[PDB]
Image 1 (cartoon, rainbow, N blue to C red):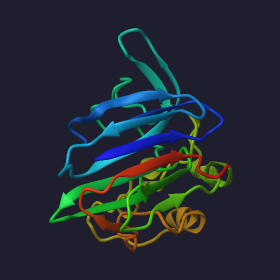
Image 2: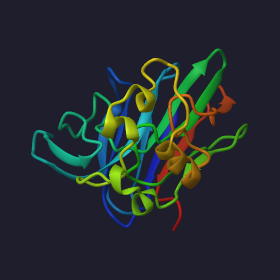
Image 3: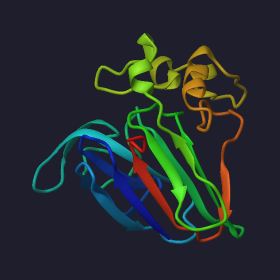
Image 4: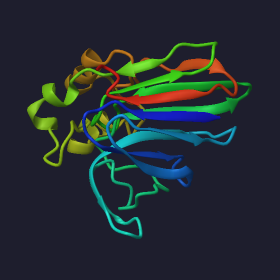
Length: 207
């Protein structure tokens, strides 16, 4: 499956793509304002994620650091990124269908639209100014808006026991972005797409 990653932000971002234990395609690449990078994700990929990283610095070997979404200090991500990270999540060819969603469970750093480029289903989006409106206690000194689990480490915010409910913090993310997961047990906003669909992830879709 092809995923065209487009940076419509006025600032540079370092796109990342991983499934947790492996890097999807190159795993990561720099995207200056306006640039598009198309990656190929193998069919059947389960638990894949794409996100943006901001304020990065890498050397000649591809090692460095980013203020948001840093993945072990590597340009080419092999693991998931450090919160806060707005997440485009997907599982492909799962019993004949594809499943996509956007999640704020690990915080928010850059606005994003995640849509199919093929017929059969609609896209999801979270482009509200969550960083600007971020509650004081969730503001990440390094940039972005942290999720409550990351900040407070409680069973309720992290839903560790699998028995949690909405919170004042999750409701903030849900208010700003109704079409994205605001907490673990949030009402699903996952979209079902035809198996083997193709997609486009656009950072800062609202220009």
